Image (spheres, grey):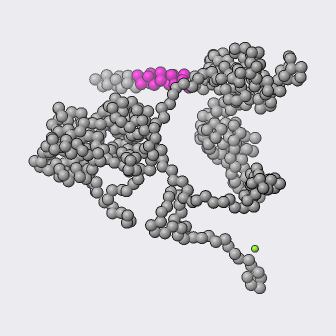
């Protein structure tokens, strides 16, 4: 009946395991927008760009 | 040999390779792992 | 103080980055670089 | 050739698709004899000789390259009004003496690209090569030399074109259809190991790597 | 006789625009299925991603 | 422990706890076998 | 140095021939630094 591995208990998982799916979904979400983001960058220009990360 | 070679003589070059039997690949990659689990699951969205 | 070291962050949200130097009195850097996590060339933008 | 200044145009095509000079073509595309689109700029009729030579055949036995003829034909009458010449029809339709039919170009795996040099030579007036003498030149010749083939029959190279060929996904099957040997052979780059003989490691930490200085392994082991 | 040639000119263009739109339709359909597919592979510790 | 249980709970190792698994269940105590299809 | 000491001792660059004529070499061997 110990924490996690006992009868009825459920393992919690490490932080990098609980956030694994949300981690890969964020990278997938970004690549899908990569083409449209490069077009805006190659169109607006390297100098007039202002949408920088934070 | 004496350099420079005459401009009209064939290039002198060495093979620089060793002969080995070619490796023919086998298409036998299983779909289920040793633990009886699928090695990959495919999902498709719907619009 | 005339030069600063900036960090160009991958817009693929992989966490990879490049570091380059550029004067303070210059516009932020933005380049198309190779990301070894996704193994493709993506857009990199300055951190701040 | 020691020197070569072409004096006629030669454009070769494979299955209707014109190939650029010096292009790497798939083994499946080059399995059939090409079609030459020639053009001479001097008057009169003459007899041409076409030779396709592979210049980069690897000979691992002697660690050098050898030459190999993939097509040979002589006594091809040509005039400045003629345009197209299909090498398939050099015996039946077009007048000529084929000394060697078309051999599909191929390249074993690991070797660099092979150059298939297409030469068009001009025979002197009233100099018709004998059909047998042409086929005997290839009887016991494994390293074809255009230099020797030219002076023997007194030819003059006038036209030229080129295309390359390397190992591709179709190279294996192409050798099977035509029964070409060597497909079960791969070439790996020769390695030249260091010529320096082994020595004894030098340094404070390198001398003390043995169990003798076990009390000092806190300074000699797991060094970044 | 010039109207016929112009109709042939318009027909060849309108025909291409039709076959060009049909090809663009299939491409957008194949890009939609590729970008929507999701292959979850067994990486380590019995995890899929 | 989590690791020790997962080790003897999978049939790849012929673990003596593998009989506790279902034919479609995973040995991991946290991860699960995802489902394939259009949904 | 001089009235004001000025330590001036550079590391030797060792330029020139590293291989002489008819000497055997393999790929990557330096033959001449200049
Ligand atoms: Mg000083």
Is D90 drawn above or below residue F20 in the view shown?
A: below
- E24 inside magenta stretch: yes
Q: Residue at x 41, y 53 (%)?
A: B14
> Residue E38 location in percent, x, y?
63, 24
Tally the marks.
0
Q: Residue furthest front?
A: D212
Q: Which residues are magenta?
A: E15-32
D131 and D88: which one is in front?
D131
Q: Magenta stretch mostly in which secondary structure?
A: helix
**For residue D185, what is the image quadrant?**
top left
**For residue F33, what is the image quadrant?**
top right
Asked if residue B7 lies left or right of residue G26, the reply is left
**For residue D77, what is the image quadrant?**
top left
Q: Residue at x 68, y 32 (%)?
A: A27
> Residue E35 location in percent, x, y?
60, 26
Q: Quadrant of ligand 1?
A: bottom right
E46 and F15: which one is in front?
F15
Asked if residue D102 lies left or right of residue F10, the reply is left
């Amino acid at each position: 009946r110990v924490k996690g591995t006992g009868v009825g208990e459920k393992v919690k998982g490490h932080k990098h395991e609980r956030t694994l799916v949300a981690k890969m979904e964020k990278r997938r979400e970004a690549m899908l927008a990569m083409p449209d983001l490069i077009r805006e960058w190659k169109k607006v220009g390297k100098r007039n760009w202002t949408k920088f990360p934070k | 040999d004496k350099l420079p070679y005459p401009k009209d003589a064939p290039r002198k070059r060495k093979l620089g390779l060793v002969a080995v039997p070619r490796k023919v690949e086998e298409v036998e990659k299983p779909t289920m792992s040793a633990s009886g689990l699928p090695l990959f699951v495919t999902r498709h969205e719907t619009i | 103080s005339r030069i600063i070291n900036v960090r160009l962050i991958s817009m693929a949200m992989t966490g990879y980055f490049y570091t380059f130097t550029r004067p303070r009195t210059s516009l932020p850097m933005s380049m198309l670089k190779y990301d070894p996590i996704v193994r493709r060339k993506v857009l990199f933008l300055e951190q701040k | 050739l020691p020197a070569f200044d072409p004096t006629m145009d030669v454009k070769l095509s494979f299955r209707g698709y014109q190939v650029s000079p010096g292009a790497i073509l798939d083994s499946r595309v080059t399995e059939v004899a090409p079609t030459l689109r020639m053009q001479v700029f001097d008057k009169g009729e003459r007899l041409l000789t076409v030779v396709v030579i592979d210049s980069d055949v690897p000979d691992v036995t002697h660690d050098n390259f050898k030459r190999r003829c993939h097509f040979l034909a002589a006594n091809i009458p040509w005039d400045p009004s003629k345009t197209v010449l299909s090498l398939r029809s050099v015996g039946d339709r077009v007048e000529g003496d084929v000394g060697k039919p078309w051999l599909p170009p191929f390249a074993q795996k690991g070797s660099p690209y092979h150059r298939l040099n297409v030469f068009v030579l001009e025979q002197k007036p009233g100099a018709k090569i004998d059909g047998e003498a042409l086929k005997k030149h290839l009887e016991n010749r494994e390293n074809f030399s255009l230099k020797g083939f030219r002076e023997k029959f007194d030819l003059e190279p006038v036209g030229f074109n080129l295309f390359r060929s390397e190992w591709d996904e179709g190279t294996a099957e192409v050798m099977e259809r035509h029964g070409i040997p060597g497909a079960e052979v791969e070439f790996k780059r020769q390695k030249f190991a260091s010529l320096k003989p082994p020595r004894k490691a030098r340094g404070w930490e390198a001398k003390r790597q043995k169990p003798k200085y076990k009390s000092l392994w806190k300074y000699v082991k797991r060094i970044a | 006789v010039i109207a016929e040639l112009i109709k042939e000119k318009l027909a060849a263009r309108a025909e291409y625009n039709a076959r060009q739109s049909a090809l663009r339709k299939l491409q957008q359909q194949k890009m939609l299925a590729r970008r929507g597919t999701r292959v979850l592979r067994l990486m380590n510790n019995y995890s899929y991603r | 422990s989590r690791w020790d249980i997962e080790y003897y709970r999978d049939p790849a190792h012929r673990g003596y706890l593998s009989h506790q698994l279902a034919p479609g269940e995973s040995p991991s105590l946290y991860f699960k076998v995802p489902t394939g299809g259009e949904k | 140095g001089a009235y004001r000491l000025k330590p001036k001792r550079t590391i030797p660059k060792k330029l020139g021939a590293k291989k002489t004529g008819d000497q055997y070499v393999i790929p990557g061997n330096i033959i001449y630094k200049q």
